[PDB]
Image (cartoon, rainbow over all chains, first blue to last red; front, side):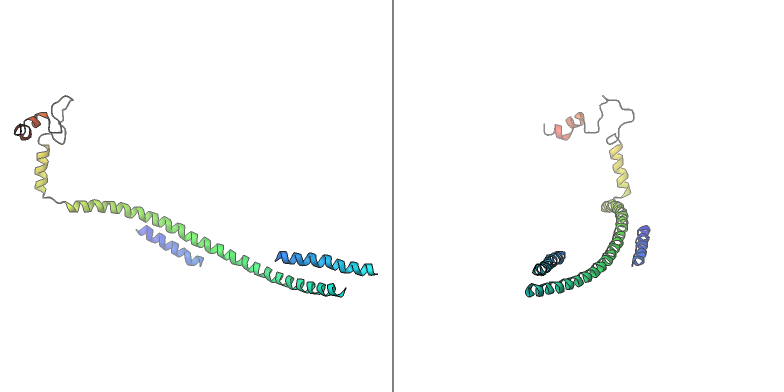
Length: 19
Length: 158
């Protein structure tokens, strides 16, 4: 669960960096 | 618009040639005035062509932005998919153990009843074989012919 959470987080951390 | 441009081109070409040629063979104001009209309309179409070239350059920049946003969308998608798959297998194995726990919740017996029933099931070898067994030994994990022929079922009806 923790890994999935941080995975989602870093992908969200990627997306404004595309924006 | 290329078709209209090229038709105006070839029309202007050979009809202006005709005007020149009738001047040459003389030594026609109506087809002159129409040549004037064709020349003006051709220049207007060339101006529209330069404007549409500007439009196409804008479109090229715009579709480059399209492809960049598509790549951003897909890079969200694939990583969200792999997170989805890992969490799916995790919750699946967890729901397997939860199903087994919920089956265990349905049946709850006192311990001495389990011990007593285990004694009745394995005092004589009914569910687990005797330790020194060779084929041809009479005892079996089913009722057996003698217990059937000597029970109430075989005797009391017959």
